[PDB]
Image (cartoon, rainbow over all chains, first blue to last red; front, side, top):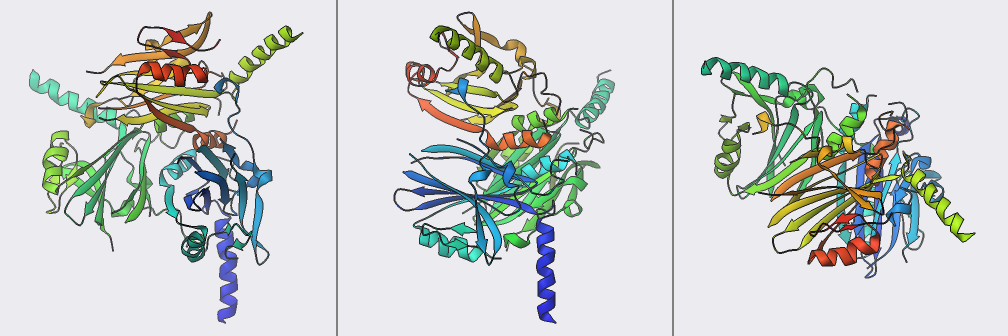
Length: 179
Length: 179
Length: 179
């Protein structure tokens, strides 16, 4: 029956993504004073991060991870003689839910130009058991990065979030994603 | 005799390049609809990769590795919930030969803008025996990248491929390189 | 007494920076033929590097590391079949001193456009004891990079070096930094 096969094939996808061959994804949304939105997305195996400068106008930031991330591994960096190299910010991430299922994890914060870097490791319990180290080194080379700008959030939502089934939270706290 | 010394000095160079202090090199050629060619070259120790977006016009791609690469380690990446993090494409690479000697390895494919990443590890049998891991981390910092554009393939061949002794295959399937 | 607490708090800062949670910093200064200066700064944990091309006019280079670097780990890269992947240049670095204390390490050299990469590892004796390898991989993602251009060295010194307490050596061999 075409109802039963569809259901098991969803359970296979979950097991694949939660294996160490599943990707970890991160998005960084920079909300600008003219109402436009810049989004940087990176996807990779084993671990993933973004490091960028948001120059001129940016007013707030939202960082979204795929559900494969281990929230406790998330780290973020933002006088040189007296500063810590990162903060562990996982406790500030909110679950994005769709039909009861976690589709992502969101950290939104307002800015008082900023340089920002964020990093997270795949959930799999084998992650801190370094598969060979050289496989992780190759994953750093194979990571794909995407960057584009949208005129307003409505346009980002209808032509970037919705058509690609990405997880998201908009200004009205409406949540997006596919369970 | 100046004939004998020249020959042994070639055997020393082979042994050096096939040691773990030899570089791995990669080139990515993007062939555009106006007949121009964009080339990105990266050279590094232990392993090497490229990750770029080719935006506007690009019609085909050729990826060339130096003979120090282990062809079986080559990996290439090109809905998020349902995609594999890379394909192992080494079996698609063709040997480039000059006077009977492998001067490079070539994967050419036509496109139906693309984002693309490719990665390969040095041939040396010690590669999967991680020298210290910190030496490999430094190699990631020391990798040098070069990018330029040429008006036509003839110009790339005469002012980039030939003067630098690089391996290549042109549109007429003529092979270049120095044995 | 407010004199005693200030002194011990300096000894704590030294111990922190010389721990593996202290940052390693690197600056690359490119001196151009119009008297302007381009500076690239990167800061990170465990290790740090820069890899850039300085295109059009550049006439000399100065590379400055924070005192947390292990000078013997410094490496620099600048026909493909016959070149070494880096040189260990630590012996060319000069100590920058302020009130008897090392505030940095400087390698200045004149050029005869250049592509250049430099890499150094934190001093801590535990550095070659890979904390988990995945922590070092995350440090690569969290590294922050800064780049700007100044009209003349006097402006770089008064609006970049002095206000940020960075170590430096100017054209008159005057040294800057905070002990």
